[PDB]
Image (cartoon, grey):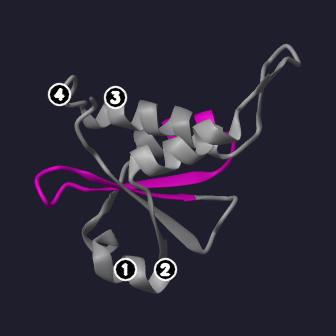
Amino acid sequence: NFAILPSLQQFNKVLAYEVRMLMTDKLQLEDGTQLVVPPAFRREIYRELGISLYSNEAAEEAGLRWAQHYEFLSHQMAQQLGGPTEVRVEVNKSSPVVWLKTWLSPNIWVRVPLTEIH
């Protein structure tokens, strides 16, 4: 049952929040509060996002090369993940594909297709 076809901007917001949870077992709040992130959630986020992991070489052949740097999306992502990030978007394939690299894994590209939300 379809629910949402998100804009690229909305998708980036969604992706950032979920990747932030992928990244840790505890969300650290401004006030020093730590919200636990159940492992099960992290496993399901990874699957539901349809993340593929690419080496630099493989990425450059699988769609990264046509992907263009998005400055606002990159900063928006960097701010949520809390570290230097690059977001590129392959607007080929008509349905966008987001390519993400972070300071945490400088030799891995994260490939995430924009999809329907259900």
- How busy is the neighbourhood of tag 3: few (under 14 within 10 Å), some, or many (20 plus)? few
Left or right of 7, for residue 31: right
Q: Nearer the viewer, mark 4 or mark 1?
A: 4
**Horizontal relation, residue 59 to residue 23: left or right:** left
Count neighbours of disc 2 (C-alpha within 10 A) and say few if under 14, some if 14 to 19, many if 20 or more. few
Residue beneath disc 3 = 10
Residue under label 2: 56
Look at the image and tell me whether residue 20 can be seen: no
Q: Residue 50: x, y in percent? A: 38, 53
Q: Is residue 92 left or right of residue 103?
A: left
Where on the picture, by quarter, is residue 27?
top right
Q: Is 81 included in the stretch rendered in magenta?
A: yes
First-in-chain label (1 vs 3): 3
- Residue 76 in picture, x, y percent from top left: 50, 35
Mark 3 and mark 2: Cα distance apart in space: 27 Å
Rendering coords of residue 97 (x, y %) = 28, 55
Q: Which residue is mark 1?
A: 60
In the rendered image, which residue does mark 4 sit on?
2
The foreground one among 43 and 101 is 43
Which residue is located at x 42 percent, y 41 percent? 73
Q: Residues within 10 Å of mark 1 (few under 14, many from 20)?
A: some
